[PDB]
Amino acid sequence: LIEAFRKEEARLLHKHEYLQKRTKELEKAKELELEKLNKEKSSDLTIMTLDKM
Amino acid sequence: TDAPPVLFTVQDTARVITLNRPKKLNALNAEMSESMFKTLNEYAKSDTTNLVILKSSNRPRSFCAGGDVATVAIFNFNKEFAKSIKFFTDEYSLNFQIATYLKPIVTFMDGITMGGGVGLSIHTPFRIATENTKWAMPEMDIGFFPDVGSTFALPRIVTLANSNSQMALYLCLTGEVVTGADAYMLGLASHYVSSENLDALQKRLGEISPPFNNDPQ
Image (cartoon, rainbow over all chains, first blue to last red; front, side):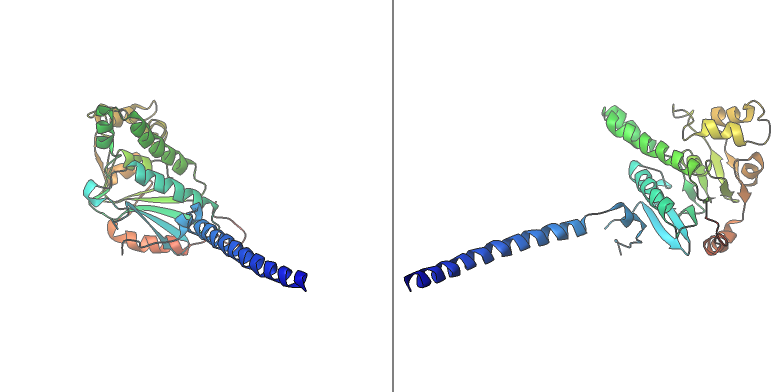
């Protein structure tokens, strides 16, 4: 029972840390992915635009 | 926010490039040249574009009064020689792209076509002139040379008194201005179309497409 209570507490704390790390990774990956999407390619020259208007 | 120097638009299967520097008579700077050079490479790869049409938004006032050499002069006075060499690498590279372009390019020389403007049309087999056309190469008065491949085109396209490049030398060394019909008869313009008929012509160019299994090239 002592091993059960101490393993459960460790699991809970280790699960919070893993989620925090995973979320930060996902957030960084989303920023990178979005930056690639916003990167201008040469094909974009063939898309008509009316930026000024 | 500011109006783009060159405007690109779709005309059915034709892609219209319009010079948009009216206050400068559509003078060509490094920005304009680079934009046109990059967009033409994309149109060459595209399989939905059959031809390109190079016109101005200032017609009949001017098509292109020439490369922007006044800015290149300030660079020389400021020793910004890298900037000057960029201006000529872009312009001359665009003149080489137009000359070797595999799809039909149709230039509407509806107005003053002097200097860089000549480079935009002289290298296209479809260079249309109008009553408002004013072809000239006024470089001898500014201290420069006949650029934009005019020393390779004029000696090969002029029609009269050009057996030994005599007429080509006359236009390049004297800076004589040729107007409308005379430009067509000398070989400076491949076709002569009234300015009023340019709108209709543009629409027809966008509507024509290669038949059956023939590419636009």
